[PDB]
Image (cartoon, rainbow over all chains, first blue to last red):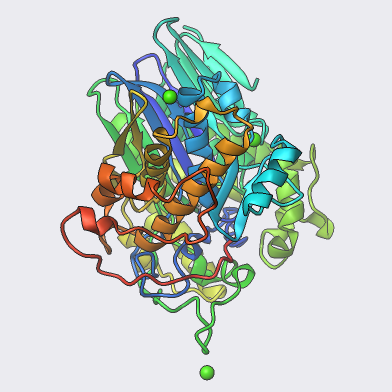
Length: 182
Length: 361
Ligand SMILES: [Ca+2]
Ligand SMILES: [Ca+2]
Ligand SMILES: [Ca+2]
C-alpha cells in the first residue's frame, strides 16, 4: 500500500491510498507485461457467513483511510497511510497528535504510534518509554520486546494565514514533499 | 526533503522520483488530479511492491471549483468464479495465509487504471500521454532502487522466485540491492499500449487476456469477461466532527473512515492531551478504544452493495457513550466484543457474526 497527496493553485486537494495488498501482491508478474497482480481478495473473511465473506463481484473490505480535514468548509489537512488494519491507527493518531495535542505536522506523524486490534495483537513504534511499556504490560497489555514501524503518513497542511502549503513525508519510507512556486 | 513549503502547490509521496514527477505536472500548469495520475504511474514503476495498475485504490478529491468532495473507488472485485468457501480446504480449515495470498484465487479484478481514467475524464487538463510518459522513461531506461524496494525484494524473494518476477527482481537468483538499476521493459511496453489505446487494452484487450491467463495458471477463475464487466464507482465521503473540524474519510467498502471517526469520537471525551504523549494513560486509553473499534470492524463491515453496515449506529453519540463505559484507567477490559449499533438505527444485519483466525500478514 502507499498513500500520497497533492494540492494545487486552484484549491483542488487529492488524498489517494492505493495498493496491491501484500508487498508485490500475489507476487505473480504478468509474463510479457511486467505488472504485479494484487492478492486483494484475501482481505475477505476466509470463513463465510459474515459481512466480509467472499462473493462473486464483491469488493473485499479495506482499511484504507484517505482523509481530508476541513475547518469552516475549507480543506486544511490531508491524511492517509499504508499498513492494512493499522492504517486506522496511523490516521487517528496523526489527527489526535495534530488537533488534540497541537503538535507540528511533522511531530504528529513522527510521534510513536501503537496498534492493537485484539487482546492477542499489539504493535508499537520505537520511542514508547521502556518503563511505560512494562507498566502497560503489568496492567494486562502485550507490547513485545521489539518495536516496529507502523504506517507511512504523507500529509499536506493548507495554511490560509500564511498563504502556503506544507507537505510532510513520514520517515518510515524514503518519501518526500515537493512544494511548487508560480 | 521530508518537509516542504510552497505557495502554488504541494506533492507528498513515498518515493522521491514520484514526488518530482508530480511537482513537474503542477510546475507545467497541471492540476492536483493531473499530478496524482502521473504519481500513480510513477509509483507503479518506482514502488512496484505497494501499488499500480495490477491493484486498486480510493482517490479522495476535493474540487476547488464545485467545492464538492468525492472518491474515485477502484477497489478490486472478486471474479464470477470466486466462491464463499474458496479459502477453505476440503475439511473446512482456513488455507494458511502464505499459501492463499499467493494463489490465483486471491487476484481481484484490478481497478486502478479504470480509476485514473475516471479521474482524468472528470478533472484532467493534461493529455493522458503527458502523465504516463515520465513513467515509461523510468520503466524503459531504469532507475536505481531505494532501500525500501531492496528490503521488499529480499523479504519476498521466496514468493517472487516462483513467478515470472524472478527474472526482473531476482537476476542470477539474487535479489537486487539498494542502488542497483531496475529496468522494466515489459512494464514500459504495457504503459506504451495504454498510452496508445487507453484502458480498453487492459479491460477489453491483450493485457486483460494475459491477466486472465496467468490468474488461471495460478489456479484462479478470472476470465476476460470479469475484466470487461469492471467499472469504478464514485463515493461520497463518510463525515464526522472532531475538535471543531469536519473530517471527510472513506466509507464502506473501507472500514477505514467509520472506525477512524469512531476512535476519535470514543477518545474525544477523555481529553488525552491532559496526559504526556508518551504516558501510560494515553497508550492505555488508545489500546482500550482500539479493542472496541476493531471488534465492531470484525462484526459489521463489508461491501455495502452486498451487506448493510450500520454507519449511523456505529457513530451514534448514545452508542459512543455506551461503548465509553467499557474504557477506563481503572483496568484493562478483558471482555472485548462488538457492541450493538443496530440498536441505534433502522433495520437488521443480513449476515452472521463469524469469528476468523488472526492470520493476515
Ligand atoms: Ca482537546
Ligand atoms: Ca513512525
Ligand atoms: Ca473431510
